[PDB]
Image (cartoon, coloured by chain):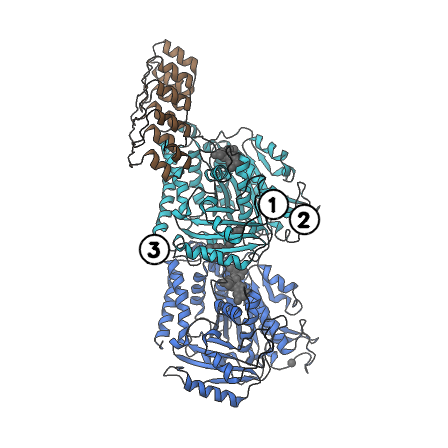
Amino acid sequence: DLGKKLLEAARAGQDDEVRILMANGADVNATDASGLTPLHLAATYGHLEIVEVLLKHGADVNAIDIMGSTPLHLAALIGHLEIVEVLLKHGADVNAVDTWGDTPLHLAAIMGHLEIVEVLLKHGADVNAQDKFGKTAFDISIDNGNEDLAEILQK
Amino acid sequence: MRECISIHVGQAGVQIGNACWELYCLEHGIQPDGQMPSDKTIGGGDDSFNTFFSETGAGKHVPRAVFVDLEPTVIDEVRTGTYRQLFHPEQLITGKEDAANNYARGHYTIGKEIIDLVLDRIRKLADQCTGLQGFLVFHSFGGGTGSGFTSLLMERLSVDYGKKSKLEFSIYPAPQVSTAVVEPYNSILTTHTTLEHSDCAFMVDNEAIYDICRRNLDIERPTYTNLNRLISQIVSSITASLRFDGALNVDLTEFQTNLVPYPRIHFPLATYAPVISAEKAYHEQLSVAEITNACFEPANQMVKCDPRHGKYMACCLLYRGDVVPKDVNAAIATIKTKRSIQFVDWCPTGFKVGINYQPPTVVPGGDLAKVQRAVCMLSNTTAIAEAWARLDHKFDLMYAKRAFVHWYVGEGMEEGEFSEAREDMAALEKDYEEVGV
Amino acid sequence: MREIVHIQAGQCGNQIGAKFWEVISDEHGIDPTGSYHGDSDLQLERINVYYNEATGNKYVPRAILVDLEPGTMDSVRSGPFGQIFRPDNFVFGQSGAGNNWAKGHYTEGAELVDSVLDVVRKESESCDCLQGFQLTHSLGGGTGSGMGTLLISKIREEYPDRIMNTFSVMPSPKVSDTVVEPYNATLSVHQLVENTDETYCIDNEALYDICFRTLKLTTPTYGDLNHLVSATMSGVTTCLRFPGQLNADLRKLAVNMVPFPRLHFFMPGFAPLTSRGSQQYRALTVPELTQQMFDSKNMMAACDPRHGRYLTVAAIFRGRMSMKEVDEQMLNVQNKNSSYFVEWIPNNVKTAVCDIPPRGLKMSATFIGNSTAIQELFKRISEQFTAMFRRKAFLHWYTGEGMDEMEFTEAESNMNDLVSEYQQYQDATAD
Ligand SMILES: Nc1nc2c(ncn2[C@@H]2O[C@H](COP(=O)(O)OP(=O)(O)OP(=O)(O)O)[C@@H](O)[C@H]2O)c(=O)[nH]1
Ligand SMILES: Nc1nc2c(ncn2[C@@H]2O[C@H](COP(=O)(O)OP(=O)(O)O)[C@@H](O)[C@H]2O)c(=O)[nH]1
Ligand SMILES: COc1ccc(CCc2nc3cc(OC)c(OC)c(OC)c3s2)cc1O
Ligand SMILES: [Ca+2]
Ligand SMILES: [Mg+2]
């Protein structure tokens, strides 16, 4: 079972191991206990090379774990702009909602990733998307007094 | 004669004490080093000022005073000040860390570090006295040392001198010239634990003194020196009968007899007049009747309140200067008729009168112009409860939220003592109601 | 209450820590060698509070430099006042903390904390009346946050009767977008809430906003931010180091500023706000100083005071000015904005004046507020912490060092309770 070894390789960023494991039939869409796939882990820890390799060999760009998190969710949370670019280029759901009602725009704005906020917006990010508490990305900026973010959300 | 020992606790009590003894020496002709040229006895004489000054073998007159503070910055100025050679060096006692505006530290944590040394030094002075009457304690209500340590010292003095009298000169807090936000807490705490171990307490509202300096002395922003030199003038008039040949209030016992009808309602109101600016050095002298009428003007009171809202339980008129007794009787005869000065139904509607024919002394460098006759009216009125109400209100606003209470519980104090102190205050305002107001 | 023992840990702790000594030393006449070279006699009265006087008439800072990374100690010595510190007071480890709170608190920091306590023990034994401890650090790093709170806990046990004072720099995505910093800050706040008496919250969010929008510095640098920090620290410590009419200490400040034990996080303010090489215009008047220091734009914590209510306030006016003009202007701002001051705390605004002005200014006003609006700083950190913890991102860095996930929940739960407590007294009434 190269599944758990591919998940561990994508997390660590060992590109060579990812190439060999995939060459021995490793399930590119393998999942751990919580439902995370190799693409989730590669995007969470900023392994752009591993993200593309996975997306070039049949990785589900909109896969969700038990909590409803998509690869774009985690990339927009950690602040990996380049990975956000690639994910969106391969059909990532820009308005995917997780178990907490959060969209990628919610997480990027909460973590102050202004540039990623712009990219998500230019790709059709829903500014009226509410979370479990009814807060949109703009509500968060107004509640935390982030003028820079507030100006961006008013394109 | 009969000696009196003065105790000064905290920054307020020590600086007030500095002004009082600065004025005392002038009134008695004593130099900053205890030298008095016109003394018949060289090594000891039962004179009038002898009650407040001891005599050494070389003719040096040393005050029967003790200065205490939990930190040295204030008392160190007395040791290096103009009166460095005046007081007993062993009577200037200081600690390292103060009470941090915390009543609990002054009474428990820090106060216990030095309580025994302060009592031993007091005994040194007491053993020098042939007939000790009691103590005059000076302190503030809001300070951590003036409130916490004072109550601790008063409790000890009651056990070691259960037969002696104890008079207070307490500084009532004022927002205009304050130092801490927990001053209402300390005020209620010390008053509660001290109400029982004191015979007579003369409160001095810093706001009233503040208003008098700005209004009668033309001082924009009064300093502590301005307030103190004025306060010492009131204290001097109250202790004048003790330091001279008094016919009214000849000893500490006489204060309770004439001013304190009940042991718990022992907070007389002081009113001093006239207070004229030193710049108006050429003002017409006010007659005995004019300065006597000024005493019943609220502007000259030492504690902000309204005597017209309460009944009188006692009144003493202490005149000083060129005052003829015939004019005093005439002035009082007019006060009894003109003004609606209402006494309680169980106390004689009379006025105790004492006259010190020595002209009032003003300190050089002071702001008061020398007058040829002044008066200080010590009146026990139920209107003083107003000052207790204002204090209790500020106490209630904070204790309702239990704010700052953790600082006291962490310094060896229990929260129950807060409710106890407040209950005792509530029992005091009611005692003032049961006598009329 | 005389000596203060200063402690600075981590990169941020030693950076602003060095700036602090360069400022107050310049304000006290001490040169990079320790020799007094001033023209005023009032700058040596309270000098013993921060400096140990060497026999050769020298004045050495009573500070201790700590860091799990030796790279920061070297840069300190190269700095102007690098040689004024006691070389023995340098306690720097080999391997850094890697921006990991767990590394600084439980593993690498634990191996070095004992060595730091020995130096702290030495400084404390040779004190006449130890006033307390003063710590400068950041909450988003590894050494300052992890090993900093460890030192605080250890010093709280060995010196339980002394005051614990901290200058905690809060993280912000505007300065460094390291998604683990909300972790390190939330875990450090849990410690600061329990083991410190006073904490000055220096928020990088507010420091950046001041430089970017107010000072019009497009690309703010750490030097531009620390220029504000050094000015804030100098003002909030002016009354501890100079004589004045107050003779204030850390305990009297805490007694009158902290109405409740856990609500001890102060919101500092300064005026006038200037930049490095600016000092533009002709100073400013007392009325201008009063309105600026209460303005949200002049606050060092990214919080709006008009969105809360002051519990206590302390303002220091440094410079030659009419003490009467200060009393009225302070009186006007309180009766005007009477709603923003709790009614159940009478006379909750104290004002002091120091003729010695701060060195390129003649008039200045520093402000210390205990406002319920500080909850916005903790809410911002809590929102970022919850966003990271919900996805369990980077948790193996901390668990791998021995930490348990229950410590994260306990940390977030405690910080949320702190926000609840602020809202309690923000909506309470005397009634
Ligand atoms: N009239 C007058 N009042 C003073 C003076 N100094 C301080 N006070 C008042 O005293 C109150 C505070 O008590 P302090 O006596 O200063 O405090 P302390 O006795 O030194 O005790 P600590 O809290 O430990 O410092 C304040 O409300 C001041 O208004 C003074 O010189 N004259
Ligand atoms: N204002 C300011 N903030 C700093 C400085 N250095 C680091 N920081 C902040 O501190 C956080 C990083 O912690 P740091 O002190 O570098 O890690 P440490 O060396 O383990 O203590 C980041 O959020 C930075 O914004 C500095 O010189 N000035
Ligand atoms: C809110 O009400 C009160 C609060 C505190 C007090 C006195 C204690 C103070 N200690 C300091 C120390 C300060 O710096 C070290 C400082 O900033 C420079 C201060 O502000 C000027 C003060 S005020 C009295 C109050 O009535
Ligand atoms: Ca004699
Ligand atoms: Mg004092």
In the image, residue C403 above or below residue C161: above
Chain assignment, label 3: C
In the drawing, what numbered circle is on residue B398? none
- Residue drawn at (46%, 61%) of the image: B183
- Provide residue B341's location: percent of width, then percent of height: 40, 82
Q: Chain letter for brown, please.
A: A
Image quadrant assignment for residue B33 = bottom right
In the image, residue C113 above or below residue B391: above
A77 left or right of C49?
Answer: left
**What secondary structure is marked by label 3?**
loop
Quadrant containing the C terminus of chain C in the rendered view: bottom left
Image quadrant assignment for residue A43 = top left
- Name the amino acid, label 2: Gly
Crowding around mark 1 (Cα neighbors within 10 Å: few <14, some 14 to 19, many 20+) is few
- Name the amino acid, label 3: Thr
Residue at the spot of label 2: C38
Earlier-in-chain disc, 3 versus 1? 1
Image quadrant of ligand 4 equals bottom right
Which is nearer the eye, C22 or A13?
C22
Earlier-in-chain disc, 2 versus 1? 2
Q: Colour of chain B?
A: blue
Crowding around mark 2 (Cα neighbors within 10 Å: few <14, some 14 to 19, many 20+) is some
- Provide residue B17's location: percent of width, then percent of height: 57, 69
Residue at the spot of label 1: C360
**What secondary structure is marked by label 1?**
loop
3 vs 1, front mark: 1
Which is nearer the eye, C4 or C390?
C390
B293 left or right of C354?
Answer: left
Residue at the spot of label 3: C429
- Provide residue C282's location: percent of width, then percent of height: 57, 48
